[PDB]
Length: 450
Ligand code: NA
Image 1 (spheres, protein in one colour):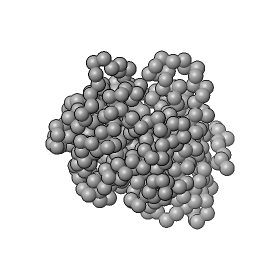
Image 2 (cartoon, protein in one colour):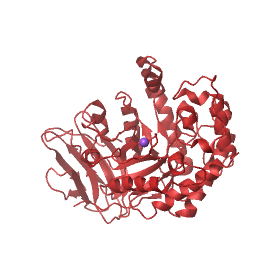
Image 3 (tube, protein in one colour):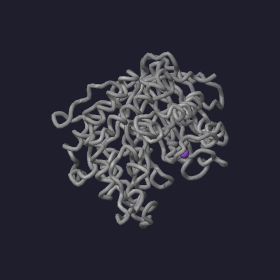
Image 4 (spheres, protein in one colour):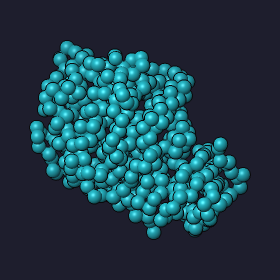
């Protein structure tokens, strides 16, 4: 008898459900980049969704786009919105929190990418201008001029985008399982971009933040409570720090329910995939990804807002641990890149799923303390400080790591769920801390880190 899904509300760095619990989101991306968008029979099937439920994922970052929403100047495609909300409804019905991602790569279809409709941008690539495709096409001069039109609002592209996202926000208003709208995927600074290296670009980030605030105000005009997800400018992904929410250079946040939405990629991993460069360069992944997490802690410290890693992974099993362990350390959730529609087989049964499919606290009736999961043998430990809530702590138990069943021990509380349940429910005995251990019956188990 599943817990009805609610809206999520930011309270400091916590995402808090309607029962007063602190929520941890683990999930996947699902993004349609090509017209026609979300056409019948090519969206997530009941079976696709069963895969996600079975492995205990509770969030989908669902792609939409400016092009999908407004495929002709000033005209909302209301039929696209019907199809999108059909997908949203199928997901939230099965307990998935849906983050609506306003997606783009390479600005637009004019460059072989996606996102902005061609009618909205004047700049176009030349026949003689080399296009190396994704991801290096961000170095194309004509693509950079496109981005300048965006940040300059030269032809009202941001005004139109505001309208488009406002229309989306209006359509999903009042739906409990919608976690928010992510304003723009991987924003590129355009011709300004070398100012971001090698130490960040305070000036551009003032421009970018004003743009995001403007889109936020357009969204909130239509749907006054919907959360908004803000990415750092994408030179983040080339190790440059963000200057968001950093007065006096950029304004402090005065908008409620804003969540930070960084990506966490290993450069050499991505270079090997898209450029065919040597895979053994991934020896650099750990120090490089440690830098990103340090940048995240800095945002957390000065802004005191939540963070969700909105994409990472991209099929490389060797880099996952970097994200997963650091996220666990900070009790930060994530959405893996990428989960496609119409799986004939379950894609989480190999090396990738072994690490993504985890035992973890979907919702905690308390302040999270330290947590650890061992993805080889399933050992799990978690401690938290009880807080008033109207539902118990719910911990999803991996369906992959316990072939002989699992055992549970609780100190400071009681397990109220049945033997072998996919969800362990835990009620606190009192005000003191609760420690939960879940493991194979013959394991000595894990210890809470400290
Ligand atoms: Na499509």
